[PDB]
């Protein structure tokens, strides 16, 4: 299965000169720079989407339906109506607040919500990231409250210490009263990725009824549909079975910007890597014009032996592909090791300079994940070879218009 | 990133 | 009659000046006939050896070889004419150094798209007739200058050519080894009916040929030498 | 002709083949550096546009730097506005700062205290929605809440809230009482920022923390992005430098870190194009071996023959950085007039482009230097070789 | 006095600790007005000798005295002034720059010695009228033939009164038809201003009109035998 074009012209590349031994080295690192960073760059973007569905998407409520200054009391009839809709899986109520912690002279804003302990597992992956042994001790009526790990970095407390939070006051008339101040205790701290730790706190549903003087009144209903790609249209028709109009929202207006910026870098980093190999393909052009005048005493020989026009063109086409085969395939072998072992590599540079990047204050995570996909390996292999076809076509066209009788032959 | 818009919709 | 070449005026613009190194050559080439064209050291030799092959354009008339002119044939048809009907022997070691001594002889057979059972068998027959079968799997860089010229001679007579164009067969090898290949060149005229011309600037290296007509600045029909 | 014999030996060597492709090979190193700077200015100008619109909505609305005391409060009779003569300060205004907590009848919120002066000019004055500036009398305890702050609290105009200061709590042998007062609201303001949920306007004269004086002086800098260099200045006595890095120290620090990652990724085009100069100049010596030794016989020292190939690797970097910085400014300034070449407009909210004139000088001077690092090795091989042992 | 006397110019090459001896125990002497003709083999000692006469190689075994100025304690920039003014080099391998025309190829040693442009347009064409190559000036040495660009390199180094011209193989490519248009005008420079040169060739017909005949046999010059 060996052709005259590829394997029979392989011995032409075994040349010998002066400083030509450094030319094959400098034409390999320059073209592998556009492949090695693109392999570890596309695998790092796949790791962001993997941690989005596990630590961001699986912990937030998808749909939220609230009244317009009413304590919603008829939530028993509005539970079976939204459950039998073909496209919404489960539902669970929530009573959100805007309390804050006053313990140790530290100011920190927190969002206190009240859900059911025996119902929160059926619609979200929230208690699957608790730093304790389990979460089965989270019961109602025992004055318990579970706060995040990032809160305790500012409260300077740990598991088993008493906490003092603030509760918004309830009043049937618009009048100001003295705010309440109770003393509770934490039962297990937890972190989610690096972002929702200092902005989350949950209480039992039965404890929220006695703290706010409400019998069986809730404020909102949280659900979860099948696909998260169309969460704006499936939330509009879900609230039309209770009353005329309610407050409708989703995660697109709050956390939907993380999926928007994950596609913008894929249109910039892939566009920048074409310009890297596009300049790196000029080294193949510079070594192909010099290969014409080097083998100028051999093209005119084959024309006397009886070579056609297409035989002379296709020698230098696959000659430049051999220089591109040694550089593009060497970026794949160096790209797998950095992608599969990115976790000790990034941690080694963070303990060198001291000031580590990607802190858990503004970003949604704190570490750099990695997920290597074999579909992007075939995409970068056909891209570096297509740019080598363009670079080795125009010097190959000039190698056939030369005259065999002009040279000393 | 750094492009934060943060506009809601009722 | 094989080749009756007429109107061979080559007006090449060598520095915006049309040269007159060849002017109206009415030379006749026969089947199995040995014509030794004796020319000067710089007048018209290598220009004439490149026009009968098909490398350069005839630009005055045509070279009607076997009833087909070069000016009327395409570049692809003239490539098939230089493969199975012609042979090229030079004096500048026109062999590929990236290949071995076996692939240099088998190179016209690999270009013409023949069957692989006939490439290796016919390449060993030409080296055995010359006497280079013991160094068949060698490279043309460590051999002597007199031994590498015999590989390029056996490179031509592979697929039974009709006219072996020879540009100074001696010069790279000695006259003792050039006498051993002359009985091989005479025996192949009785085997396949081949023909060849020996062009030499000297007077003592073309006495064994049949016609001894000379050449004086394009006047190749001058029999007076 | 040329009076210098150092530049005349290369002006006829930058392509001599009369062909449409023979001249394109010698100019391959020019386009590789030109496209490197062109793919660096137009991308970093959008990152500078996001940083310019972030400091005008967040840093341009809050007090950036304040010169407060180091052992308590400040005395304006001892340290007046004539005493503060720091560089970069454009205006001095008295203000106080304190982490407080709000209190209402529906919900409880958090925010800071900004004791602005109603007799001076405030940057939040055109952002007011039917609120008067002179309505903050010293003694009526009026407070102006934000739009996002009053939205989650349900406090309309004419109501009354409670502001408690947890930091300035007076020590008592019984209990723990905070120094809190009673404030009434007058209206909200829409500022189109994120500071409408934790900032409020109040009079400077208040007895909610101590006693009556102020804590510090509010200043406005010409550049709030490099306030680290202005912290080691000779300060007057009885003062302590306080910047905006105590609250927003991680917001704008991540924007500067992203410019060092995108700019480093796009700098690989210049590093690859620097490797093309080793291919373009290292192959020229291997073919022109005859033109080197004859120049050594004509009377040229090996020091002078090293500088012949220096400009051959530097003139492509000079014309590559000038044309690269020129086309980087033409593409960035003419991006949002016609149909955008990025495909679909993902934002659609008047995408700004900020072209800093100082940043173009740092980019062009770096790209003219990496072209000189890849020249010292091919020029040394043509100079340290022997004139009688290389070829003849 | 004597112009140049080479004493013990032993040039021995070394690779793999192997003594490659091509020149040993020579006592060649060059004088003002005296013409030499070094006729030897094609591979014995010719070009290895002529590279040491101008200082293009290190002998590493002795020293060569030249007008009271050796090259044993000199730098790389100190030998550049001697190789331009009083020294000349003529080769046969077509060592002409193809990207430069004949206007500045002859004036290429003139631009090195900081000569002003008032004398560039009046010195590089003084050797082109007698040779007949002045009208073929605005051209290019790339597309010319073999018998056209050979006469340019002969009068290339004769721009600043060279005291020693190291000519080597004047006929290697061109025919002897046009070679007799230069072989009598190149030796007249010794009787009206004073200089010296030498002709080195391996053929046996370019040393018949000389004044001193001597051969070279791999570094042996004792007598005059066949
Ligand atoms: C979301 C971004 C934040 O950056 C921004 O400010 C967005 C504005 C710029 C977005 C592209 C602008 C496109 C329009 C310009 C005109 C067209 C140009 C087209 C391209 C030529 O997040 C980021 O991208 C910053 C984080 C860094 C991610 C990319 C770098 C990956 C990590 C660094 C690797 C460096 C490796 C170098 C050594 C091997
Ligand atoms: N393209 C060309 N290449 C070489 N010579 C050419 C060319 N065009 C014209 N000529 C002329 O041909 C002369 C060279 O001699 P040529 O006619 O090729 O026969 P030749 O030299 O005797 N062959 P040979 O003696 O065996 O090397 C030159 O001096 C030119 O006058
Ligand atoms: N680097 C070298 N290159 C060539 N020859 C060398 C070299 N080093 C040593 N030699 C010796 O020099 C011989 C070649 O002859 P050389 O001394 O160069 O004078 P030459 O050949 O007579 N010059 P010329 O006859 O005009 O080509 C070789 O056979 C070697 O013994
Ligand atoms: C900003 O608002 C959205 C932040 C989401 C991305 C956070 C990480 C940014 C840097 C990503 C670098 C990935 C590639 C690293 C290996 C080359
Ligand atoms: Mg010939
Ligand atoms: Mg010599």
Image (spheres, coloured by chain):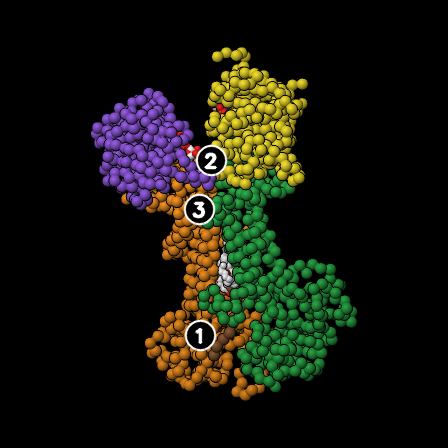
Chain colours: A orange, B brown, C purple, D green, E yellow
The answer to whether residue A1 of the structure is visible from this angle is yes
Real-space Cα separation, disc 3 to disc 2, in angstroms: 33 Å
User: Which residue is depicted at the point 45% across and 76% down?
Assistant: A249
Q: Is mark 2 within 8 Å of ligand 2?
A: yes
- SS category of the residue bearing label 1: loop
Residue A61 spot, x, y in % from top left: 43, 72
Along the line of sight, which residue is nearer the eye, E82 or C204?
Answer: C204
Instruction: Please tell me how crowded label 3 is: few (under 14), some (14-19), or many (20+) other residues with Cα within 10 Å.
Output: many
Going by the image, does A164 lie left or right of C149? right
Residue E47 spot, x, y in % from top left: 52, 25
Q: Nearer the viewer, mark 2 or mark 1?
A: 2
Note whether C99 is above or below A130 in the view shown.
above
The chain under label 3 reads A
Mark carried by residue A284? 3
- SS category of the residue bearing label 2: loop
Going by the image, does A100 lie left or right of D236? left
The chain under label 2 reads E
Going by the image, does A336 lie left or right of D271? left
- Residue at the bottom extreme of this rendering: A173
Note whether A55 is above or below C104 in the view shown.
below
Q: Mark 2 — residue?
A: E145
């Amino acid at each position: 299965p060996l052709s005259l074009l590829i394997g029979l012209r392989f011995s032409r590349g075994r040349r010998r000169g002066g400083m030509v031994s450094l030319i094959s080295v400098i034409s390999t690192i320059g073209i592998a720079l556009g492949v090695a960073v693109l392999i570890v760059g596309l695998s790092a973007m796949n790791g962001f989407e993997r941690e989005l569905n596990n630590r961001i998407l699986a912990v937030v409520p998808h749909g939220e339906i609230e009244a317009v200054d009413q304590p919603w009391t008829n939530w028993q009839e509005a539970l079976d109506h939204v459950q039998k809709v073909p496209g919404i899986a489960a539902a669970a109520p929530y009573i959100n607040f805007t309390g804050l912690v006053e313990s140790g002279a530290n100011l920190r804003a927190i969002q206190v919500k009240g859900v059911n302990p025996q119902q929160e597992q059926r619609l979200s992956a929230l208690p699957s990231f608790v730093q304790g042994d389990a979460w089965r001790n989270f019961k109602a009526g025992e004055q318990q409250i579970i706060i995040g790990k990032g809160v305790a970095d500012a409260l300077k407390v740990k598991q088993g210490d008493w906490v003092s939070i603030m509760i918004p006051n309830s009043n049937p008339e618009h009048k100001l009263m003295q705010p309440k101040r109770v003393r509770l205790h934490v039962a297990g701290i937890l972190q989610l990725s690096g972002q929702l730790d200092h902005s989350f706190a949950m209480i039992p549903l039965a404890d929220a009824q006695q703290y706010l003087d409400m019998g069986s009144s809730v404020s909102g209903i949280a659900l979860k549909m099948t696909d998260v790609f169309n969460a704006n249209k499936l939330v509009r028709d879900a609230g039309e079975v209770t009353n005329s109009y309610v407050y409708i929202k989703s995660w697109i207006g709050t956390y939907g910007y993380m999926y928007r910026d994950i596609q913008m870098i894929r249109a910039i980093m892939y566009l920048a890597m074409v310009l890297v190999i596009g300049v790196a393909c000029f080294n193949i052009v510079s070594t192909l014009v010099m290969a014409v005048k080097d083998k100028s005493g051999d093209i005119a020989v084959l024309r006397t032996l009886g070579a056609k026009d297409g035989l002379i063109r296709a020698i230098f086409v696959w000659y430049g592909l051999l220089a591109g085969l040694f550089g593009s395939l060497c970026g794949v072998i160096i790209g797998v090791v950095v992608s599969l072992q990115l976790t000790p590599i990034i941690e080694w540079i963070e303990k060198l300079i001291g000031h580590q990047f990607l802190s858990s204050d503004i970003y949604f995570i704190d570490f750099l994940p990695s997920e290597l996909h074999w579909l992007d390996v075939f995409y970068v292999l056909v891209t570096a070879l297509l740019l080598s076809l363009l670079a080795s076509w125009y010097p190959a066209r000039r190698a056939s218009n030369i005259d065999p009788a002009r040279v000393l032959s | 990133c750094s492009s934060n818009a943060k506009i809601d919709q009722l | 009659i094989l080749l009756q070449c007429d109107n061979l005026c080559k007006r090449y613009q060598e520095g915006s000046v049309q040269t007159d190194v060849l002017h109206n050559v009415s030379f006749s080439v026969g089947e199995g006939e040995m014509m030794a064209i004796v020319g000067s050291s710089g007048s018209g030799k290598s220009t004439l050896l490149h026009l009968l092959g098909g490398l350069d354009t005839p630009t005055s008339g045509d070279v009607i070889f076997n009833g087909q002119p070069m000016s009327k044939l395409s570049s692809a048809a003239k490539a098939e004419l230089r493969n199975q009907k012609l042979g090229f022997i030079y004096q500048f070691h026109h062999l590929l150094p990236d290949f071995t001594a076996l692939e240099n002889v088998a190179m016209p057979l690999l270009i013409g798209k023949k069957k692989p059972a006939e490439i290796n068998s016919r390449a060993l027959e030409m080296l055995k007739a010359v006497g280079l079968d013991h160094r068949a799997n060698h490279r043309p860089s460590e051999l002597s200058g007199g031994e590498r010229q015999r590989v390029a001679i056996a490179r031509a007579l592979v697929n039974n050519p009709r006219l072996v164009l020879a540009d100074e067969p001696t010069g790279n090898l000695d006259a003792r080894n050039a006498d051993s290949i002359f009985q091989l060149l005479g025996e192949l005229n009785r085997l396949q009916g081949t023909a060849f011309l020996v062009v030499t600037h000297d007077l003592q290296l073309a006495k064994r040929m049949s016609r001894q007509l000379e050449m004086r600045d394009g006047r190749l029909t001058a029999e007076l030498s | 002709y040329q009076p210098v014999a150092l530049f005349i030996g290369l002006r006829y060597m930058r392509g001599r083949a009369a062909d449409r492709f023979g001249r394109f090979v010698s100019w391959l190193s020019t386009i590789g550096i030109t496209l490197g700077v062109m793919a660096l200015v137009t991308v970093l100008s959008v990152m500078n546009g996001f940083e310019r619109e972030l400091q005008n909505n967040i840093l341009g609305l809050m007090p950036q730097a304040i010169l407060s005391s180091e052992h308590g409060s400040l005395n304006p009779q001892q340290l007046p506005e004539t005493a503060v003569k720091l560089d970069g300060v454009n205006r001095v205004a008295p203000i106080t700062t304190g982490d407080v907590v709000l209190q209402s009848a529906r919900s409880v919120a958090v925010g800071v205290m900004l004791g602005i002066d109603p007799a001076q000019k405030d940057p939040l004055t055109p952002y007011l929605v039917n609120v008067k500036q002179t309505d903050l009398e010293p003694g009526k305890y009026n407070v102006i809440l934000g739009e996002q702050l009053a939205s989650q609290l349900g406090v309309n105009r004419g109501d009354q809230i409670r502001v408690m200061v947890p930091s300035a709590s007076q020590f008592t042998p019984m209990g723990r009482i905070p120094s809190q007062r009673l404030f009434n609201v007058i209206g909200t303001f829409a500022a189109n920022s994120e500071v409408d949920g934790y900032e409020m306007l109040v009079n400077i004269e208040d007895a909610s923390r101590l006693m009556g004086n102020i804590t510090g002086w509010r200043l406005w800098l010409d550049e709030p992005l490099k306030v680290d260099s202005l912290s080691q200045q000779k300060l007057p006595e009885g003062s302590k430098w306080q910047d905006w890095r105590d609250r927003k120290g991680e917001l704008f620090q991540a924007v500067r870190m992203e410019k060092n990652m995108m700019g480093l990724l796009l700098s690989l085009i210049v590093a690859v194009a620097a490797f093309n100069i080793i291919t373009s100049l290292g192959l020229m010596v291997m073919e022109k071996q005859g033109e080197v030794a004859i120049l050594q016989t004509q009377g040229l020292t090996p020091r002078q023959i090293m500088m012949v190939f220096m400009v051959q690797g530097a003139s492509a970097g000079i014309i590559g950085a000038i044309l690269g910085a020129a086309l980087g400014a033409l593409l960035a300034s003419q991006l949002n007039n016609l149909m955008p070449i990025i495909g679909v407009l993902l934002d659609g909210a008047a995408l700004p482009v900020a072209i800093e004139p100082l940043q173009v000088i740092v980019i062009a001077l770096v790209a003219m230097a990496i072209a000189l690092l890849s020249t010292l090795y091919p020029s040394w091989r043509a100079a340290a070789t022997q004139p009688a042992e290389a070829l003849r």
